[PDB]
Amino acid sequence: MFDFIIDFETMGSGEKAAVIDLAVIAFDPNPEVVETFDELVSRGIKIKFDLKSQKGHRLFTKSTIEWWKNQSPEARKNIAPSDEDVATIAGIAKFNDYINAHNIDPWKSQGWCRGMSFDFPILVDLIRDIQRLNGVSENELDTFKLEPCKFWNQRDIRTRIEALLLVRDMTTCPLPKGTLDGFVAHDSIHDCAKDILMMKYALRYAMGLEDAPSEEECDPLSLP
Amino acid sequence: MFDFIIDFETMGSGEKAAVIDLAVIAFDPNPEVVETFDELVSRGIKIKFDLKSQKGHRLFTKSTIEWWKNQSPEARKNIAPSDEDVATIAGIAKFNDYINAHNIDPWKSQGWCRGMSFDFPILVDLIRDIQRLNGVSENELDTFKLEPCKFWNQRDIRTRIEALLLVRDMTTCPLPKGTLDGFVAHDSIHDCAKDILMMKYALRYAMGLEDAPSEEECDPLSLP
């Protein structure tokens, strides 16, 4: 029984926000199982969307367009159009296929993102497109069976880590030295891998299966 | 500096969902203060929405209507129209007034709901309505200064309680005897006060400030 992480890059903010990419990784919640960076990254997939086709269908917020304009050249590159872009209806199909193929229990697994109010409402809006394509009226939408986890099993990453470490406003977690060797800063799959690791080590410390390293004794990439 | 909790009752699922009421309670995050049920309730407010005014504007989901059809008559009484009903712009104004009168810091306070992907997107869609009321286009909405907490300060109650107690899928917390004395079933404000109390004590049981009551020696309104 694996859990999973998801993370969207978008051009807007609400549940109809134009989506740039969607990274997802299944992982083992067992506190004594410490899945490493490389295997997490390898198990993960990145679904990349065709932005143009969402014009007229999804929401390009201008305060987000400008935000992207000011970001770094390598961050802007990761979000440029490429030949791997897929329509959103193809992307959500790929997303469901990954879940069905990766030991996710529809009733017992948990889904995680860095801000539940952001990724899950978009995810669900995309899954609702699956029913809209099949002619379902908006007020008759019912995606309870199509969703990758039960809604009461979505989980917020900021809330988890902050609660595990008992430090208000602390939503990252230091990892032992070299845990993030091979990290590429604007690789969607890596970002989810680091968040998976930070949540596992927070779980081990709060249980007492290892101790929090020092500032000079931990991978500096894990340090806010 | 207080934190706050919110909770809608709705007739719908997405961010456009038809709203029935909105309970909100400002409360003290500090562990060493245990505020009583009676003062939490007395600090809370309930905004009840006029359902008829939302027909054609907000989403009435068939399966949510059917789920309401099957609740007890006590639960359904809260749904019926009432003299205290307000238009959605009126209720979001009242919500903003309550937040402004109750020691909430925009940059530091944390907002709480049972299911971050449910209430906060509806809250934000109601606040967006303020900007559409001003003639702002959908693609130029920007509610960042209007939101009661910053988006990264939203927090999920299910994730919190489960993290503090270290039991997978345990989203309630046992309370010492008499803690819920006075609880009235299906009172929107009472439910939020219960959740504030369950979050506080879960923090205390994690910090060693008290030991959890035994399943026989706890308030039975806190059991699963």
Image: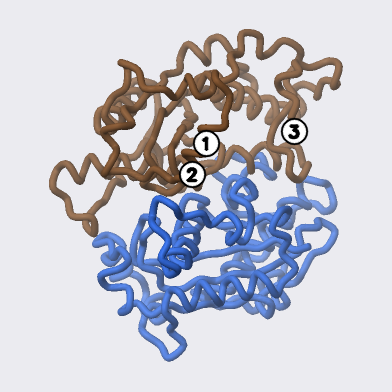
Chain colours: A brown, B blue
User: Quadrant where the C terminus of chain B lies?
Assistant: bottom right
Chain under callout 3:
A
Q: Does residue B152 appear left or right of residue B213 in this picture? A: left
Q: Does residue A89 appear left or right of residue B208 in this picture? A: left
Label 2 packing within 10 angstroms: few (<14), some (14-19), many (20+):
many
- Circle 3: element type: helix
- Identify the residue position indicated by label 2 in the image: A118
Query: On residue A121, which mark appears?
Result: none
Closer to us: B31 or B122: B122
In this rendering, which labeled residue sits more in front, label 2 or label 1?
2
Same-chain status of marks 3 and 2:
yes
User: Quadrant where the N terminus of chain B lies?
Assistant: bottom right
Rendered position, A24 above or below B24: above
- Identify the residue position indicated by label 1 in the image: A113
**For the residues bearing labels 1 and 3, Cβ distance under 8 angstroms:** no
Label 3 packing within 10 angstroms: few (<14), some (14-19), many (20+):
many
Same-chain status of marks 2 and 1:
yes
Residue A198, by quadrant, is top right
Residue at 35%, 70% in the rendered image: B71
Most distant residue in the bottom direction: B83
Chain-order first, disc 3 or disc 2: 2
- Identify the residue position indicated by label 3 in the image: A206
**For the residues bearing labels 2 and 1, Cβ distance under 8 angstroms:** yes
Most distant residue in the left direction: A135
Chain-order first, disc 1 or disc 3: 1
Question: Could you give the CA–CA distance between mark 3 and mark 2, rounded to whole angstroms?
Answer: 27 Å
Chain under callout 1:
A
Residue at 83%, 63% in the rendered image: B33
